[PDB]
Image (cartoon, helix red, strand yellow):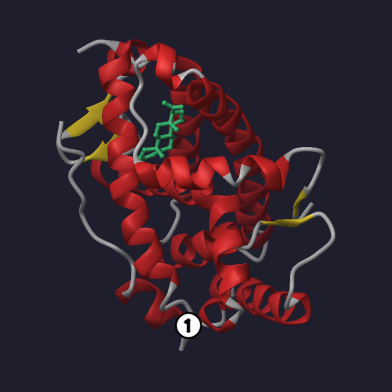
Amino acid sequence: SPVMVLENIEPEIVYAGYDTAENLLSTLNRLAGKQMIQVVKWAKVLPGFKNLPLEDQITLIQYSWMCLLSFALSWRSYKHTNSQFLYFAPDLVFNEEKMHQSAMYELCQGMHQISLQFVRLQLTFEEYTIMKVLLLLSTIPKDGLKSQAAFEEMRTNYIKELRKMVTSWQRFYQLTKLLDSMHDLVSDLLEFCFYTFRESHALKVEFPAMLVEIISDQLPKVESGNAKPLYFH
Ligand SMILES: CC(=O)[C@H]1CC[C@H]2[C@@H]3CCC4=CC(=O)CC[C@]4(C)[C@H]3CC[C@]12C
């Protein structure tokens, strides 16, 4: 039973341990590193995904960590603030002022825009959950994965699970359209993230060992079009 397993393994609260732009960004990076810990424990108990060679699991996670965390940022903003603010952590909610101080003001707007989508679609917890798994399987290597045959079977099943959900019948295509749009939002998130990373030493913006670990060997798997985003439309 996919749905029941998905809600149970869903990670829980996590403090960021909370003011210039550099300190604000350093904080979110540390919070990111702490959230990626919950993402790793969550994925390892994920149906299907946990049976693919460990190499595919790690790769998929590195291609999609930004998706998963920002998408969650939305669920959280949706649930705790009716999408009115950015709920990164309990001790750190963002409003236009904050979004401004992080030197991240447009990027914030885009995420807040996803949240707004949630309240408008009246997104469901059951939908959210399956959708977060699909985001995990939203980007693959340009020429395919090791166990590609297995990958597609699993991905098709979760797509089927989302279908079982919505069955008005159009809501399906609405949620999968929303999923494709996430790609656009995350591609901008990463470009800015890749830049701050490259200048971290000069900008005084702290990045956790984990994020450094991921972003580092992610760039090579992306550059020269070595990555392939999967869309529904
Ligand atoms: C400083 C920086 O480049 C920013 C740009 C987009 C930002 C990320 C946006 C998505 C996100 C949501 C969270 O709830 C935790 C922190 C993260 C993972 C953010 C950490 C800081 C990033 C990587």
Q: Where is residue 229 in the image (x, y as percent from the top left)?
A: 74, 50
The residue singled out by tag 1 in the image is 2
Residue at horizontal 79 percent and vertical 52 percent from the top: 233
For residue 105, side relative to residue 225 (left or right): left
Q: Extreme bottom residue here?
A: 1
For residue 177, side relative to residue 100 (left or right): right
For residue 39, side relative to residue 2 (left or right): left
For residue 11, side relative to residue 5 (left or right): left
| Mark 1 surroundings: few (<14), some (14-19) or many (≥20) residues within 10 A | some
Q: Which of 39 and 130 is in front in this view?
A: 39
Residue at horizontal 50 percent and vertical 40 percent from the top: 117
Judge whether 65 appears above or below 146 on screen. Answer: above
The disc labelled 1 sits on which kind of residue?
Pro
Q: Where is residue 15 in the image (x, y as percent from the top left)?
A: 17, 44
Q: Position of residue 84 (x, y in %)?
A: 32, 30
Q: Extreme right residue here?
A: 143
Residue at horizontal 60 percent and vertical 55 percent from the top: 175
Q: Nearer the viewer, residue 41 or 133?
A: 41
- Residue 78 visible: no
- Residue 214 visible: yes
Residue at horizontal 66 percent and vertical 36 percent from the top: 184
Judge whether 56 appears above or below 100 on screen. Answer: below
Q: Position of residue 107 (x, y in %)?
A: 50, 24
Q: Which of 53 and 159 is in front in this view?
A: 53
Looking at the image, in which quadrant does ligand 1 appear?
Answer: top left
Q: What element carries label 1?
A: helix
Q: Nearer the viewer, residue 98 or 27?
A: 27
